Amino acid sequence: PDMDTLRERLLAGDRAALARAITLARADHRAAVRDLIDAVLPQTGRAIRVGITGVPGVGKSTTIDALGSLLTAAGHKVAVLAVDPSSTRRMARLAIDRNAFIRPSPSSGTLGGVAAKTRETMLLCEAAGFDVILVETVGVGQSETAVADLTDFFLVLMLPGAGDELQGIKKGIFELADMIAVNKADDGDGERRASAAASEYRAALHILTPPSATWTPPVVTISGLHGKGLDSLWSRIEDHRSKLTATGEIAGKRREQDVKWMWALVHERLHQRLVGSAEVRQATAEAERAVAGGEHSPAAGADAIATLIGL
Amino acid sequence: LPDMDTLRERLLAGDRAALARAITLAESRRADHRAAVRDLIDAVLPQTGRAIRVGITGVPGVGKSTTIDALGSLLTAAGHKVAVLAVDPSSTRTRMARLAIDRNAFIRPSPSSGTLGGVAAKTRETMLLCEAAGFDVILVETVGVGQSETAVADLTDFFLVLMLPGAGDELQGIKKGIFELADMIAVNKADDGDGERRASAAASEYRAALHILTPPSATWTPPVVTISGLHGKGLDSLWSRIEDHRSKLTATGEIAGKRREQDVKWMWALVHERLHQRLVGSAEVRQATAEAERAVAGGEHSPAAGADAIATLI
Ligand SMILES: Nc1nc2c(ncn2[C@@H]2O[C@H](COP(=O)(O)OP(=O)(O)O)[C@@H](O)[C@H]2O)c(=O)[nH]1
Ligand SMILES: Nc1nc2c(ncn2[C@@H]2O[C@H](COP(=O)(O)OP(=O)(O)O)[C@@H](O)[C@H]2O)c(=O)[nH]1
């Protein structure tokens, strides 16, 4: 409590109020903050939402720290969030940045739950006046698609070498990308290496059909460590925002995303009621085991689960 | 209902009439009929799974019906029994001429359900019945408009994408989401002469891009091939590549592993379809569900508030 004061404080720009709200996001504490979000929904959405991914070691934290510091220096308020699978189990300079709000990936039993708390945290930050939301993720199962469905622009960071030199990435990320940035383009030979690799990705991306006629994903080279190409990278993100806002496509994407998250939440309530209940959790596991083990057909397993939903 | 023990025998004996009967019973409006079929399937489960399951997709007009008709006919001539199953999202609302007359083929349209998940899950059950009846090749095709590509990929062992022969400025391009699903790209309409030169030119562009974009050392590297479904070119080679995939991924256990993941997916799909039935069961709940979706879609209420409203209705 009390939720009327918290809201007025949040909308004013109060960091402790944002912190408090985020903390709430206990079942009755969860629910209180959801009514708050519905109430400030009209003051959300005035932010550029960017998803960022890439292989461990590519330079995500380094690049985020460098870009976020450029952005705060230019007068933005930057929220840096995360969707990390490891949360179900240091960007040093941005931390000291009072105009940045870093939040580690929230704890939750499922990746759906991690995704759900992050989307909540994002709307809270927007209501609090943050105008850039960066969402960091790693390529684990479904997290990349989840983050691409949470943001306006999905940035994929790549090591400076394609084809035979690729490792540790899921193929589909090239289709989620609104831009590929090849990192480690350090003065000298790094520039040549990264540029060679960018030219290959550029040639390859030509076979993938862009989802919008309004935007053809660029391939750029950057050095997050040495601060090369970062302003040009951001300029492309701003270009995308401008062009797709003009056609109504940012709004359009956001609406689709919202209805997707609505249905995903319904299925999430359902599942964790079946998995939480000391009454039916074992029966649910037994049905999944019978199906996965080929003892009973998928439909037979669904039949057993139906009875548990009865009760 | 008929005697289900006789029906089971006839099905396992490979009787095509029994298969169609079991399918008709699955499509019945009576729940008690649909239940009998579910029990039959559980009973014949140990006799299922000895088939190559292939998903096939491509844009309308690429020549999918023609290619399936041709390939299906080669396979039945080679001693196989072939089922062709469609998956179409318009099954949730509201022509292969030679194979249609082939006694060793079994063709069925997309089953009705409330959700695409439901349609696909009912397709998996149909696939099990076909396999129990001795069908050793199951072709599952996407039909109409819709994004049923993922559903068809998650129903099968191998996902084949058919593409148009355009090259250079006329290259078709791979649609978003298909690149990560494709186990092979076949450029169709490689007719003798100009057509096959365009198809080979397109294949070379796809092959070069795929090399750049595909991390090495996967068990299987998706090939790019050219075919003509209409003139019967490249189909035996295309099939040998699918048999190669089966061998390689059977040896690593990857085919069994994927089928396990899929089966659990389809179980949960059926659970969700049943809860969707609840939300569209009467005019009043249908309208309430629509109003929740419209509120979230219009920015008036948050996703969580819409989800609250839905959960309540059930
Ligand atoms: N040479 C070079 N090294 C970099 C660059 N960006 C990051 N690194 C280094 O790459 C390693 C991984 O960086 P980090 O940001 O932690 O990677 P992350 O796991 O993707 O978040 C560290 O040693 C970084 O200092 C760059 O642009 N050039
Ligand atoms: N020239 C040529 N035409 C083809 C080939 N395969 C299919 N077609 C034609 O392309 C049109 C669409 O074929 P269809 O099989 O119905 O395509 P679908 O909509 O993808 O199922 C028809 O006129 C076919 O005759 C081919 O290999 N060569």
Image (tube, coloured by chain):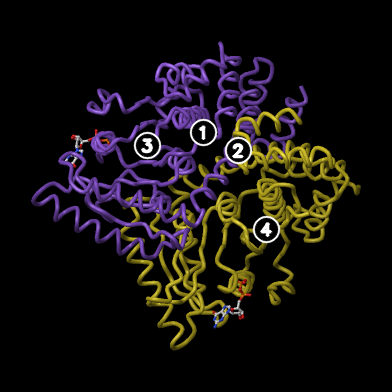
Chain colours: A purple, B yellow
Q: Residue at x 42, y 56 (%)?
A: A243
Q: Residues within 10 Å of mark 1 (few under 14, many from 20)?
A: some
Tag 2 residue: B264
Cα distance between the residues tagged 3 and 4: 37 Å
User: Given the image, on which type of amino acid does mark 2 rest?
Assistant: Val
Q: Nearer the viewer, mark 3 or mark 2?
A: 3
| Kind of residue sitting beneath label 3 | Leu
Subunit of label 3: A
B28 lies left or right of B133:
right
Q: Quadrant of residue A3?
A: top right
User: Is there a contact, CB below 8 Å, between mark 3 and mark 2?
Assistant: no
Question: Which label sits on residue A43?
Answer: 1
Residue behind mark 3: A134
Does residue A137 show up? no
Q: Quadrant of the C terminus of chain A?
A: top right
Q: Residue at x 65, y 26 (%)?
A: A284
Residue at mark 4 shares a chain with residue at mark 1: no
Q: Is residue A173 above or below residue A7?
A: below
* Kind of residue at badge 4: Asp
Say what secondary structure mark 1 lies in.
Answer: helix
Discs 2 and 4 lie in a common subunit = yes
Secondary structure category for the residue under label 3: strand
Q: Chain of mark 2?
A: B
